[PDB]
Length: 275
Ligand SMILES: C[C@H](Nc1nc(Nc2cn(C)cn2)nc(N2CCOCC2)n1)c1ncc(F)cn1
Image 1 (cartoon, protein in one colour):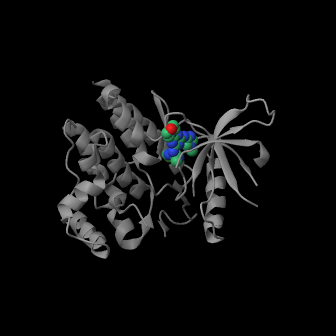
Image 2: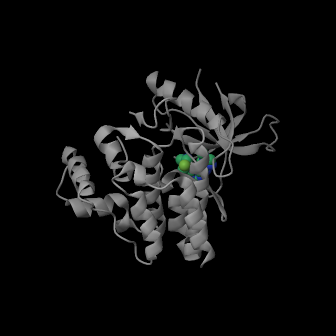
Image 3: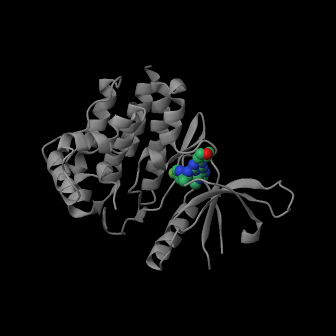
């Protein structure tokens, strides 16, 4: 890939843009997503080079496809998924997404996380805003900017954070693992069943439970205390109990008692059948 052949189309949201790669100067080229760094350092560049190796190493249906790189001024080039983040697509098109559909996505996210696990990768930022929509019947995990490799001899990796998606051990000991990704997956499942209604977001709920007066450094302490005492996001309206039970099982204070992404996929698919 050569940087003189990228035609800028629009900003998507380190930044991400929509580009055309068109070396034939003839508009035939395909549309691709391009990631780069907003204001970059050497440590911020070092991490970015790993992410790129990480994504190149991944080949899966529910994981956005690595296309290449281009320079120097490093840019990551990937396939362009036309419907954007699942977070926004649900806000846009709630009227056609039913619970079977939410479970369809849910199952696909699992499968992607399962595969990630087989490479000993920990994602660390699993939330609906990092899930892209390829089309109406398929979603993919769309960002790996915080993803880490597990050591050969350990089952966790020690490291502004998405605290309202984090497991207690991530909050208290900075430990990330497959079990922490599963916790976050619980939050993702909650998101999906709230249809991203605004007052029902994990930050809004948690703040509501902590107290909205609380500020800055204290919030994390109080969030940790809340989870310690089994405070949890409530069941979303219209969420069947059996589905909430999966959420609460993911949100177990005990790391080892949390389910595997394989167990979850099955229980989800099974539940989907029955509707
Ligand atoms: C910032 C970007 N936002 C984005 N990306 C894509 N597509 C995309 C990103 N990547 C990496 C691949 N395809 N499409 C949109 N829509 C498209 C239509 O107009 C509104 C925004 N937004 C994005 N990147 C990763 C992610 F997980 C979620 N969001």
